[PDB]
Image 1 (cartoon, rainbow, N blue to C red):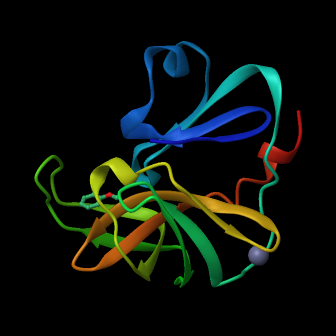
Image 2 (tube, rainbow, N blue to C red):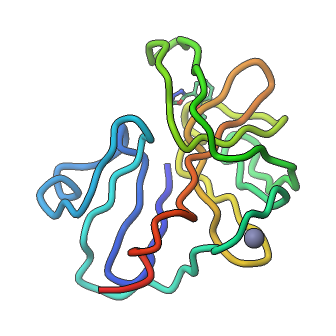
Length: 140
Ligand SMILES: COc1ccccc1-c1nnco1
Ligand SMILES: [Zn+2]
């Protein structure tokens, strides 16, 4: 689990969104596993605006933050797992690292702020849903 709280937005994995998120929907995209809902209180997370490929992510299944190199946001095949079917996911970045389903929502951060959230895993890779292209999270 986990979310990004920027301005009056809450950013979550689409597959973990709650009824409240859907009842306060701003934007969602199945292809990216992202959903954004509106918040009553202002958040303080800063979204990275950059093309960094190094950062640190939170892995809840190890209670650890790991430094990682990560790839460019791309359209990648995600294999079937115990709880989820095989599908293509867009705006996905991969790193070599540990990820289990319950790690979804863990923050990836660089020196510029939040890059994205854990979204996929398998075969010793961790996949992150990028948010750095969603420039509107910074306004309105
Ligand atoms: C961090 O995510 C995973 C790690 C391992 C296996 C599957 C997943 C996953 N796939 N879709 C959602 O979670
Ligand atoms: Zn950066």
